[PDB]
Image (cartoon, rainbow, N blue to C red):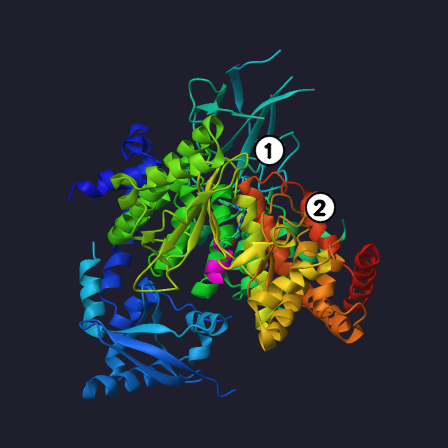
Amino acid sequence: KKLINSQISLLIGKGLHEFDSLRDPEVNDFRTKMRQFCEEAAAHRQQLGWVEWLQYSFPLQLEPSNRALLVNVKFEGSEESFTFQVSTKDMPLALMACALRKKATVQPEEYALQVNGRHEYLYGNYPLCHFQYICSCLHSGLTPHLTMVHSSSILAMRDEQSNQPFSIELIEGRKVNAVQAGLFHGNEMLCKTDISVCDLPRMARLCFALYADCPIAWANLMLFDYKDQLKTGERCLYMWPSLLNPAGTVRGNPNTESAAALVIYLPEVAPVYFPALEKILELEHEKDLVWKMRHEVQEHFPEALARLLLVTKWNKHEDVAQMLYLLCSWPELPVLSALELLDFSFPDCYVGSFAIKSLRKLTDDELFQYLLQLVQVLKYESYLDCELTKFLLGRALANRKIGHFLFWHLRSEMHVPSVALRFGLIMEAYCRGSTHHMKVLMKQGEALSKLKALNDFVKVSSQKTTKPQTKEMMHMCMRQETYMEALSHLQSPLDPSTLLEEVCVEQCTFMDSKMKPLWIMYSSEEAGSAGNVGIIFKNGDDLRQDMLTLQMIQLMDVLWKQEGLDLRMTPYGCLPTGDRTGLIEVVLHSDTIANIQLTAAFNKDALLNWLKSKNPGEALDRAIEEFTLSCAGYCVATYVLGIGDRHSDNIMIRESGQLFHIDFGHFLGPFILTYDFVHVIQQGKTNNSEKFERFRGYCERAYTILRRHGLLFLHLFALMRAAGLPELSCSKDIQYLKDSLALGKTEEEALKHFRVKFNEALRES
Ligand SMILES: Cn1c(Cc2nc(N3CCOCC3)cc(=O)[nH]2)nc2ccccc21
């Protein structure tokens, strides 16, 4: 009744009074409208069925021949566990019907299979092989553990989890040192840094830059307000430190004490708004030809809308109204085309609304893949109340996994003052819709706060004393009441399906490096070996570049699995949580190349003998295949993304044989093919052509599949420019993908070019 308001403030890292203190009507209009939208989404959520509620809380973790395996099935009420044998091609209902007959001695449509000690469920018309939990148990050799949960238990859980030419007067400034004005409609100008007042578009930006050559500060603002009315008159521009930047935020600097301010005046012409859609509908040499053929583009080339929207004159109101008439009648564009329109080059709200309309067909799995890029588009946005915010919030309240990651993508960027207001207001609105999930994320917030204090304890002690004494100091600090309660019994921020319960204090350690990252181990009695999970807590380094690289490798694996090619990739979870704060998922039963190299007689034998120890007898044959597929997959991945600084310490190998990279610090500027890995692929033989030429084929096929989806990597990386990455800021960064994948060249021309690069790495081996 009263605690909710106080709980949001602690959770989002900013007090609710701070929004009210600004006295801005736009912020107040957002808080009132979004709350009603979020509460209506929460009202429909309670009206949903028991299976529909499972689709929200526990989304199906699905995979992107008459095998049989035993399954341990138990009930909610009793501790009785009935183990029986089933088939991999069987439906979950068949497993439920078989479990029903076991309890009869000692209807299945009323049950749902819950994964023991996990926030995951098995349901729907899909064979057992299509589930992520089943396939993971098969390679580990473990038997799946499921619990029968009746419809009444899911329904009871739902009830407990409920809620004239344009001119401006340049007055004065106040800066520190020893003013260029320009009008923009996206990435390009409207006039020279010479435009009529009636010839001004709705999404027009007035950009400023203060300099002496030495750049000092910049400031951008919208000509029209949130209520479609042109701004008048006097305005104070709180400048941001630094030629002219149109991509930057249209909101002033919050530090009104130290940052520079510029006073400007907007001359009154009448209370002139912008004409509504109803009124709009009535009204080198290649660019002119494309605009001439505009009707043929709407009828024959719908995909060419992006090229048509760049050629249209935004500085003339006649061309804008003519284009908008076609846009309202324009057919629905596919996912790939809609992602291109979200870029800063297309600022118009109607273009943005058309993109959202085309993005409505996205599945919860597809939305999760591009979620990071969609959150970045919010930075490019002009106003708080927009279609992208409504779409991201509406889908976050429809799927709890989406709502989990959306929150963390907004919470991690709260320390940045340019996005602190927007991201905080979106999180506040989401909390009004999901009251129970707000409490769930609070437990994660308490755990990360304790981890920061534990990392600070380690950072100080490691300098004062040695490594074994600092480890025991960390152990004694963890054993405390406050630490044992906050760090136990919570949903993992890296994966909401994974439950972190008991923390194994003795297994917990730290790396003796510059930032001192924490190693946190867990265990669950209900889950068993599935509950044995680890988390790496890092503080001081920016993990935004590490996550993006790991998300692209995850995307590569998804695109390869779509064409029936499983290159056994290891896409472990990486997620930033705050100011240089983040988490890394531990890939258990794996070690670095350096640790294994340090019995074997030679360096080439070190990796092979380790595989012979973990996979004995005929199990070694699978480990070589697992290594060959993973090496070929990561070889293309490290070449396309351009991952440099590669040594034995940043390359890891699983006990099953799977090879994977870690520590992605530098990207986008050949691929390493050292004989140490080649020796494993060739089964230990000095000369094995039949085993090497197969590996050569896997590298060539993986490269061609990514070339076909070449535009997808180009569209997503262009949207990530808003984040402000140090290695992904200029047009030269996106050019690396155009050079590595060779988009301009044909399928055969790029494959022949790839063969030269493949032989270059083999000659250096
Ligand atoms: C070796 N070591 C590392 C190195 C390190 N390990 C990483 N992981 C990736 C997931 O499987 C486990 C290893 C990812 C990464 O970026 N850096 N971090 C540590 C943190 C605490 C203790 C030891 C640590």
Q: Which residue is mark 2?
A: 669
- The answer, for residue 563, to whether it is visible in the render is no
Query: Total label count?
Result: 2
Q: Nearer the viewer, residue 137 or 700?
A: 137
At horizontal 46% and vertical 78% (from top left) the residue drawn is 129
Mark 2: give few (<14), some (14-19) or many (20+) Cα within 10 Å. Answer: some
Q: Which residue is mark 1?
A: 245
Mark 1 to mark 2 CA distance (whole Å): 26 Å
Mark 1: give few (<14), some (14-19) or many (20+) Cα within 10 Å. Answer: some
Q: Is 397 situated above or below 217?
A: below
Q: Which image quarter holds the N terminus?
A: top left
Q: Main secondary structure of the magenta part?
A: helix
- The answer, for residue 336, to whether it is visible in the render is yes
Q: Residue furthest top?
A: 178
Going from N to C along the chain, the mark reached first, 1 or 2, is 1
Residue 100 is situated, as x and y percent measured from the top left of the image, at 24, 84
The stretch in magenta equals: 366-371
Three-letter amino acid code at the position of disc 2 = Gly
Three-letter amino acid code at the position of disc 1 = Asn
Residue 494 is situated, as x and y percent measured from the top left of the image, at 43, 53
Q: Nearer the viewer, residue 513 or 497?
A: 513
Q: Which image quarter holds the C terminus?
A: bottom right
At horizontal 68% and vertical 45% (from top left) the residue drawn is 645
Task: Judge whether residue 224 is colored magenta.
Answer: no
